[PDB]
Picture 1 (spheres, rainbow, N blue to C red):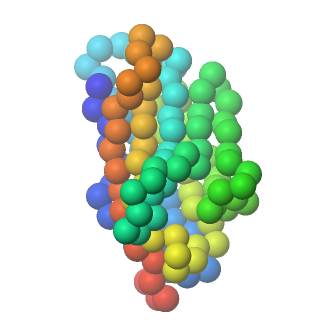
Picture 2 (cartoon, one colour):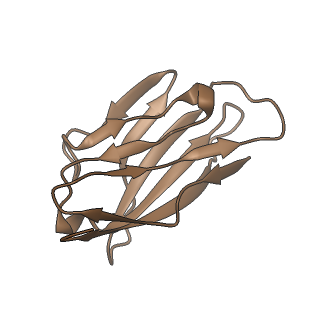
Picture 3 (spheres, rainbow, N blue to C red):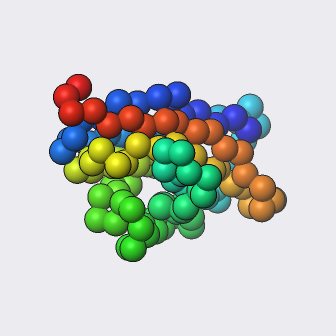
Amino acid sequence: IVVYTDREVHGAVGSRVTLHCSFWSSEWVSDDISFTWRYQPEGGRDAISIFHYAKGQPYIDEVGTFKERIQWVGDPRWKDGSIVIHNLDYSDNGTFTCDVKNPPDIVGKTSQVTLYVFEKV
């Protein structure tokens, strides 16, 4: 019922960063949960889906900004939906939203994290 990301993360160019996402519920919940990561670049307003996970299967977008640079490191059994962004570039700055969904609804719970990329870190 509650979704956790970091608030702000700093990455170095050429390096990598982990985007954490998890959730917790006071009531028991099944592993029939979906995670969706959307990306909104700095100063933009579109939230583009870069990653999805459901029915034990991950789905990485093959044409977007982070094609070939997304790694799934989550685990539905630990209620973890985290991903890693690889080979960072200055233009990767933006807001990432983790959207956690249950079977009984189409409406998820979301939490967001802001990424700034620096030359050194």
